[PDB]
Length: 50
Length: 149
Length: 167
Length: 167
Image 1 (cartoon, rainbow over the protein chains, first blue to last red):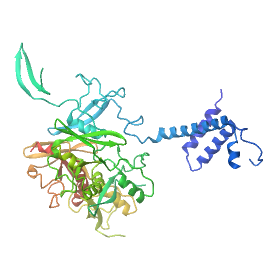
Image 2 (image 1 turned 180 degrees about the vertical axis):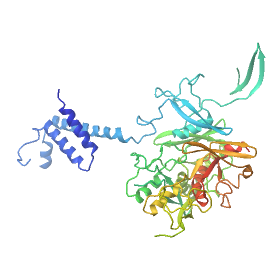
Image 3 (image 1 turned 135 degrees about the horizontal axis):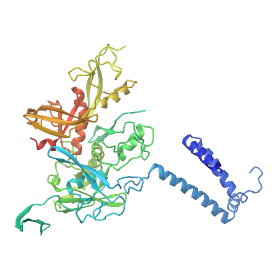
Image 4 (image 1 turned 90 degrees about the horizontal axis):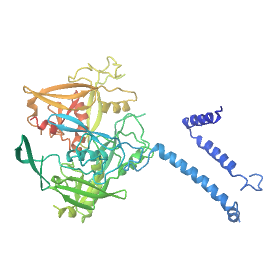
């Protein structure tokens, strides 16, 4: 058996329990990573800085 | 030129899918907020509030002692528009039935913060008595009509 | 931090400043709906917390944190119907048409109930004023918050002309 | 540090602010049960220390140190029984059912005893109010702390309907 997902869920739950002002910036980073991984390709062209 | 570049950034389908993603996330966040903290419309009782239970406790003053009693309900199944209460078989008298009178109707309306309609008067006056076959008949007037038991 | 049961505040009625208390839970719960320590804030019984709109902003100005009100100070009646010795008062509530009932025995004498009486207390939840006189309406509006804070539940306003013909 | 005998404080009754004194020992003992300088704080005789719950939190806010109250301001009656010219009043006390007795001569005239009388003093330890009127109950609750601080021992509340039929 494997239980990595349960461990990650427990980590996220314990993070939500220990709520601070800086949880929102981490949630924003996570959702941005998910969004970029989900679509990507479409709106990336030129602009090596981007 | 900036506007032209912005509008031609991605095809329409990608824009629709990206809008759907953000809309779904926003609605999930709003649902999560609505689950924990409670909604503004407490009058409708929504689902986060009680008072849907079967029994309701009230008190009344008699002679020199204060006595308590229960008021029954359906538990959530169904609603009566005429009486504005979760009544069960209120048209018949039996164990477990519900009965609301003006002496308790006002207190219950104050407790529930909404008006309710009483079903019948608390008491009536008998005017004639007839005895037949070892049984006694009591006659009284109800809403201008003759009744007996 | 605070275990106080009552909170003091002031209001102006008839050109003088009166005082009244606002009850609090005293240390249990937080009631995130209106972020105030309340005791059973769903029943109009005595001793329950009642935050009116008019004093909510003053309380949220004395205490430097937002505070959400619970009920409006008062409402205006629109129709009255008598039936078998009872009177129904109709008024709007958040866009829905509702009604409330009271005994007809309280309406035998309007003078002891109208505006600011000599006794200083109201026997019932309604008030009577003349609709033509601007000053009477203004005084009733001013005293509505005070009389809705002295005792729980909002105050219903009755126009004298409307109720004159039914009695 | 302090040898003062009386401590001043304020309360609000009928929309006005009155004042009353709280007695202290004056320099002997500490009474760690409620960390206050008290004189024989176990008897309801005159001059004894009496810290009510309602003013305990205000005193512990003026004096920046915790203060534990001793007795509740008031209690609600539940049953009354007359016997050989005496009347017993039943009320709850910390989950136990107790009773108190008084002479029936004080109940001949309820009007001089109800709520805030013109004299401003209570002849006996009970008070009478109408249970239907919210304002009367609120006024009685507000005046209960003041009348329990003017004289020692708590105040018992009697409903007018309950005592009306026994007399």
